[PDB]
Length: 113
Length: 119
Image (cartoon, rainbow over all chains, first blue to last red; front, top):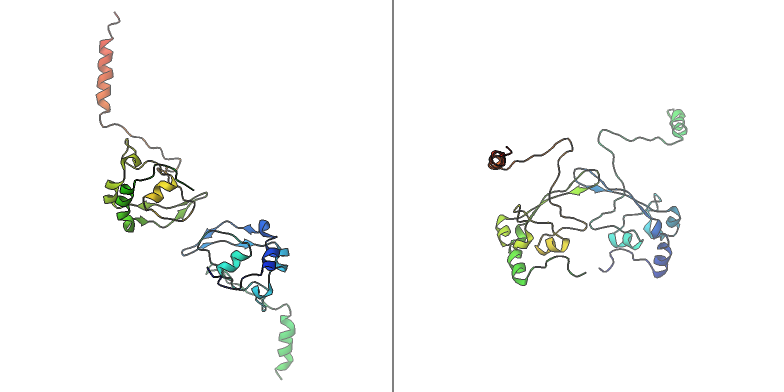
C-alpha cells in the first residue's frame, strides 16, 4: 500500500497494540446514504497514541487515513471511513453557553459606556 | 482455502462468466438480526448454469456455497450467505393445491366404492 499517513514506529506500534483486545465496536446503524458505527478505545490507550495523531486545538484525534487507524489495531471490514463528527437529525438543534456567560455579559455590561 | 461444492469446469466457468457484467445487485436492507439483498441474473445466464446447480423439483437454484456462487461470477463483500426464500410475517400462512387435486379424490372416492365390498 505504501502507508498513506504517518506510519507508527516499531515502538509506537508495539505499545498501542497492547490495547487491541480491548477496543470495542458498536453495532452499525444507517441513514439514507450511510452506514454508521463507532469504535470506543480504552482511555489508557489514548495515552500511548502518538501526539501527531491528535488535533492540538481539541484534544481529539485528527482525521485518520485507513492505514493509520488500522495501524492503531482498530480492525473492521472494508470501506469504512473515519470522520470527525456526526450531526443530529434536522429537527434537533444543539446549543451551549460558556459557563461564565455572565462574566462576559457583565464585561460588555459596563462596556456600554 | 480450496473449494466447497461442485467447482465448475473450465468450460462451464468460461460459459457463465460471459454474463458477469450483467449481473445486478439490489441495495441492502435490514431487519433486526440480518442485512439483506438480492442478486438478479440475466435469464440468458440461467440457461448456461450447470444443471446440478438446480433444484429439479422447483426450477430454481439449489443452495449455493460461497465458493459456488462466487464461481458464477457473482461478486460481493464478505459474510454474505445465499438462502432459498423469504418466509412471510408469522401471521400469514401460505397454502397451495395441485391443479389436479380432484384426480386423486376421484381415485380415493373410487377406491372406496371398490373395497366397499365389506358385505
